[PDB]
Length: 140
Length: 155
Image 1 (cartoon, each protein chain N blue to C red):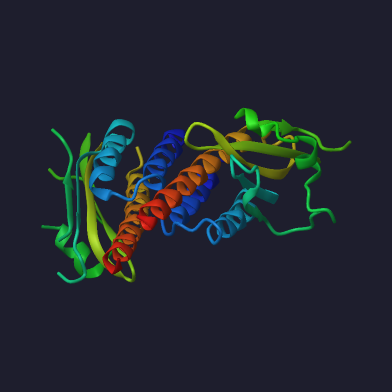
Image 2: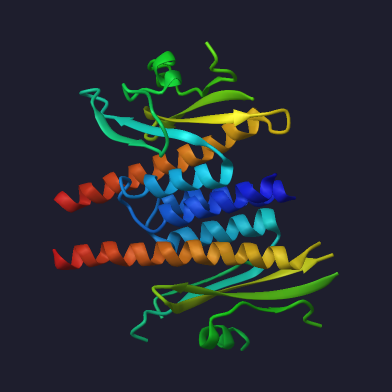
């Protein structure tokens, strides 16, 4: 399965390195996470430091604490168990959003969390870069 | 093991996604492949299709021949232009392998990525080659994207 992880990480890495548009990119990423990793009910939200710029959701109140303290929250069993993961999207020193998902497990959960956190960080950077480029267009 | 490849891939992708400029990017990437994967004397060369001149040329840390070539680079002269990975498991003339993976965007190959690896019985040279390809593909994409940004800039 650790091979499937690299494959997924690599695939999302390609999507990002070739496109500076998160609002089309994210859906592709969710698709990958859902098809390979087996996530579900994925959801992302990113707020402009001024305030809510981006929002996406998967197909088919705890997040609040991730904004406050900017640390990964997890609940191994909501009631095989269904876990709920919510990692912080943080770049520029602040937390700018949260990435969440469900993952039915039998399996190591802490690994899925470490992974979903890797995506959140990659996404955090792309968002920053997309805004930097928009800034150049604004000046001109 | 794969746990190291994941971290390394994650680290390089965390760089490519932070800036468009390749010249300040590649340096960090080479420093990772060297300290995590155990590569060395890595080199990246991207050409201009029309003039066949060098657009990008980055080399890692370490001793390079007085002439700038890597012994392996001189050997595999412009063979990368076929879009196929080249490898010489031994460069004798522990083993020292040389890997050269093609950088291809927009269909055409536009450069090469090379690295030397001190292999042994415990590590597979075939796996390292596959990994260097992933990096080559990511680098190609960023190069492509930096040009698209440079284009919309002139307009």
